[PDB]
Image: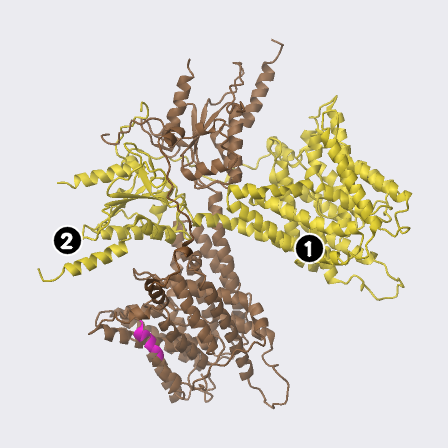
Chain colours: A yellow, B brown
Amino acid sequence: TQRYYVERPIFSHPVLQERLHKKDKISESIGDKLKQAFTCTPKKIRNIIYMFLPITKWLPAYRFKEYVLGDIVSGISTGVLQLPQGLAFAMLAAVPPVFGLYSSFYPVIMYCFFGTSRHISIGPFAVISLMIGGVAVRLVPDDIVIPGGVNATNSTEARDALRVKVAMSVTLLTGIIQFCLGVCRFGFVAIYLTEPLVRGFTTAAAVHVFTSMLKYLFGVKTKRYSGIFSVVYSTVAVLQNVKNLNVCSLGVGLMVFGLLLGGKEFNERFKEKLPAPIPLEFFAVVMGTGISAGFSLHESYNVDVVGTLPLGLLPPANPDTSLFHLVYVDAIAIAIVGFSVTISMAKTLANKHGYQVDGNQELIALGLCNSTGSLFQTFAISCSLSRSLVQEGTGGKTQLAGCLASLMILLVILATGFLFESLPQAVLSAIVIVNLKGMFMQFSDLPFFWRTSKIELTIWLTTFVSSLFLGLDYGLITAVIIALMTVIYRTQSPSYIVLGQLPDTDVYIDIDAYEEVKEVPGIKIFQINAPIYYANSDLYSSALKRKTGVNPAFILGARRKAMKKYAKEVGYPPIVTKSTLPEELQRFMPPGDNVHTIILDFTQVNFMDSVGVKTLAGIVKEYGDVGIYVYLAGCSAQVVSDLTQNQFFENPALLDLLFHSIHDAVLGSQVREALAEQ
Amino acid sequence: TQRYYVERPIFSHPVLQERLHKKDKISESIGDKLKQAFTCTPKKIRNIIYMFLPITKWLPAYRFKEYVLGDIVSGISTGVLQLPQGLAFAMLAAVPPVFGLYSSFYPVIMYCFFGTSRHISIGPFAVISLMIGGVAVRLVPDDIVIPGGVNATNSTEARDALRVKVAMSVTLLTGIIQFCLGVCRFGFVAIYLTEPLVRGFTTAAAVHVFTSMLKYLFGVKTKRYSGIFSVVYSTVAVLQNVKNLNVCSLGVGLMVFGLLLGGKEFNERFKEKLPAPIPLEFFAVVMGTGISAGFSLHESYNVDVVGTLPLGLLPPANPDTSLFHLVYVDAIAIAIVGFSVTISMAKTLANKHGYQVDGNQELIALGLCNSTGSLFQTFAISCSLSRSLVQEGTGGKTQLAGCLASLMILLVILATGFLFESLPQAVLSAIVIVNLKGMFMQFSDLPFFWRTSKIELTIWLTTFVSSLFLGLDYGLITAVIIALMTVIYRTQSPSYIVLGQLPDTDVYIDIDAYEEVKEVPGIKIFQINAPIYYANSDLYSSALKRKTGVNPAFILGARRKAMKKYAKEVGYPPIVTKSTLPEELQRFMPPGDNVHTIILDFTQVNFMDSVGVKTLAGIVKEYGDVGIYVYLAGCSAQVVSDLTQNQFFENPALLDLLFHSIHDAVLGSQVREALAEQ
């Protein structure tokens, strides 16, 4: 009770206004830096070169004597992990693996040339390109290509080249739109994608891909289906075709999968410093190819296989404007959605170390990567998670050996072509399924958010379900829409609370939560913790009337009833704001409360609008007509301006209805009542 | 300086917490009123009957000796005005006028049976039904109907019946969806449509209809065009076809229009009590028909005409489910959009007198009206503005003679059929163009909003332009989307202001606006007037760092530079929140400011989320690591809960970082500094 002594005069609005003067702070050419920019200063040019090219400044900063070795081992490990994942994803998107290797190779060096993140991976998604191949199959049948005179019995390479072409088209579209959007300084557009939304989205995608690799584990072939409920159709078709599968395929897949989990668990039991990360994928692939060569795991057992690798560089084939118009006409939505996923994933992965990274810069860098790749016969690209978890778990922070991993895979795409034609698909399916562990453990958020709140759980469940059932593009877009809608909903249902003054103090708290605060007689206090705009005004008015229990409508009606019942015989603009009491000391007083002023707390109201101003004017006019005073709380500049600009401050007297604190309003009302005693 | 004496102990968080206890207030069966509802009490049943049927209670309340006469004259005037408008709109939507009369007649009595507003009109729009007829023309050509063996040369009645059928279908759809949506207690969905949006939308519609009636003034026929840029095509086609028009048609139209404006202006110059409202439409129609009969204003002059009226009652033809599926498959969007326009217009017109009106109730009442009409071969319905402006300007508040106006038009639709076959279209076009005066004067909002703000002008212009160029449905839907987006945008760009304490007081105001307040040395204050959620957190962090000028990144970097430069020779979980000073009294102090605590004002933060909590934790951890204290402002229950539920309140010490006022935080920090002096 020692400190916090105030003893202050009562500032309503005008007193504090007169206590102060104004400033200017403003010059000419506001925002018009062009008249002061545009010089040949070396500083601006060199800085522009710096921020469009970071490797210039990455050049010196490189440590040694263990930093080099850690970097190199990191790059080697990440490349050897990237390889089989590239193969698997290329097989996923229904393309010969050589183009998956092209994707694994070219954008890596492109990014190393352009990119500020110290950690990176390439090609974590093929499902959207899958849906694109589905649309292309919907365009041309899988067996009716050209009935000409080539005298080919049944070759499926033509449709495959078709799918490659459509992938090139969509990826060029994506890269170009990415350059276009990045150059406009939209490092902010990524912000609209929230953590729970991304979590649920990625989990749904993991489910989709697991369902897809189920069949390539089973060996039993099946026509692929895309579109709405695509997972449903594919799953039920596979379960129908369980009859007549390959038992040896399932056996080898299960054996290798179990061995891989056993190795990973055994390594994880001895996770010490001396044990360095071991590339399980490399052992998996070498043993798979060795066993395939040993026991003749091919047409000898009639099991599936990789097939011949077109070992050799391909010059960049020109994308000819023949049907690019028509194809992007219906590829636009898919391009932009797969886009938004990629950019969001990349940027959220960027914020790992306490380091600053430019947004639009990385956008443009990836745009160059994408356009160049698609011109080099390459599909879409982004950064896969676990790969940086390697670069970081390896301890290699720099990206040098990371991009050197591309030169490392260069030998495979240049030297070893016979080494890889013989290999099944179940092995790759096992690889990806094992990789899916973290995404499948992402489910922990359900009880956590359940205990946490309702809104974030709602968004997570809705985006997950929509992405699962419907296509990925539709799921994402509806998720974003509802994400922006939840904010409106939250501002639709605020917490209307009536205050109660803590005794002999100036703090005001809700009454019905503590059974220790009491309310000052004859006054009422009403607080809304949400801005007042068009969609939220009438709720506020009605809630106020029904919560203060002072609804003037029935008050007036009961007054009329009482007066007519007591009635048994004959016995510049001077606009008054608050009417005097219409009562003439009758004896038919409607039992209830006697409140003489109402206090509207505005400490939470961030902004207003025309509709809010109209509603406030209505409230003021109504209560003054009844004969009840009202006051506001908080002479903030924004709200003062909002009232002023709108047709409110004609100052009949309304400037005399402001306060800069709740307590000031309380004291002022009490003083007015006291002065009323003549 | 007399009043407002406080002398209060310093409540941070825990002190005020211990000062109070809690309550319960909660029983079982929360929200489960079903166990206490569901009885045979006459009260609930009678009230339900009351709120599903108001005319029961309208029955007694009816005044006399001038109230009857005013009501009757109001009803007669409104009917005689409704008639020609009904004719014009029916001609607008490309339908024989008899069905326009059906629309003018049946829903009126339906509404009188079901509806609580004392003022009403019917059938203010036909443009959406026009676009529907456009789609139907897009379905079947205007001249290729059935090449059979009927031996009819060229009759256009078949396509007209087709358009009537499609109108019936869409209107049944609308009525049924209206019942469906109203029964679910959505009196709130109308709230999303704001005043400026509706203003711009209605103005755009007025422009469209004026463009449409241009040709029917010109007499020069033209194939009608709908869709995107529809106004553009129709306008340019008419201006191309200006050659070979009918001069007599234009002459009579201009003469009658000028005479009508002259009469209206002359009446408005003598707007006194004794002059009662005169129905200008009635004089217009009678003189038009008289002159048409006199000088043979028909095929004698080859000018246009109304044509024969199918005088007679039509039994309700059954809507057969033959192509209803296919037609609503692409009529859904148009139905729902024309819907939303109608409901919004009706409800906003309801709030005229200080009276309460139920929303979902009126929704269901209009749904019955619409379904019954569409079953009786009737198109869509709503309330036109000026008509109630008549009912009110006439002074007739009750709706009795208003619905009796339907019985008044009954004579025309039953007795006078020869009286109206002979009449041109330019007269009706003049009627509607004259009616458009208020909608065309709605343009005044442009400079008003220009001086007012930017957001509402933005929304008004955008909705107006989109409705003009594109179709009405597209314009409306994009307007609603951007309307909900502007709120997000407003929360994206708050007003970051740094406070300055008013001397020897406890009020804190922005420094750089008044050049009279000063800041307390060693402290800094930061206020955001917007909630902190996912889409708005990083903006807040970065703005804070760059505005307080205390960005710890460069502070740490400069500290490292200074230390290495001064370096020239060798000479339960105890988690500390704020680190001590890492400085060891060097001499290379980076020149700048010395601030020892930061104050985050939360009096505006309405709510938070997971991302906001993470960002706050990051800020706290960072600044404590640097060695800078921080504090919050406002121990509100909502924000306290938000921090608590999220992984924040493990109370290492964080409960000791709260305050219920800015001044409390200031004093507490000063006390901590003072106590630091040992």
Q: Amino acid at mark 2?
A: Arg
Magenta segment boundaries in residue numbering: B399-406
Q: Which chain contains the residue that carries disc 2? A: A
Q: Residues within 10 Å of mark 2 (few under 14, many from 20)?
A: few
Q: Are marks 1 and 2 on the same chain?
A: yes
Could you tell me residue B396's position as x and y percent? 27, 71
Q: Which residue is mark 2?
A: A587
- Asked if the residue under mark 2 is in contact with the one under mark 1, i.e. CB atoms within 8 Å, the reply is no
Q: Main secondary structure of the magenta part?
A: helix
Residue at (27%, 76%) from the top-left corner?
A: B72
Q: Which mark is residue B274?
A: none
Which residue position holds label 1?
A231
Judged from the image, the secondary structure of the residue bearing numbered disc 2 is loop
Q: Residues within 10 Å of mark 1 (few under 14, many from 20)?
A: many
- Residue A143: x %, y % from top left: 81, 63
| Left or right: residue B593 compared with residue B501 | right
Where, quadrant-wise, is the C terminus of chain B in this rendering?
top left
Q: Amino acid at mark 1?
A: Val
Quadrant housing residue A602: top left
Q: Position of residue B181 (x, y in %)?
A: 47, 63
Can I make out residue A508 in this image?
yes
Q: CA distance from mark 1 to mark 2?
A: 77 Å
**Quick one: B1 or A84, which is closer to the camera?**
A84
As drawn, B312 above or below A410: below
Of callouts 1 and 2, the N-terminal one:
1
Chain to which the residue tagged by mark 1 belongs: A
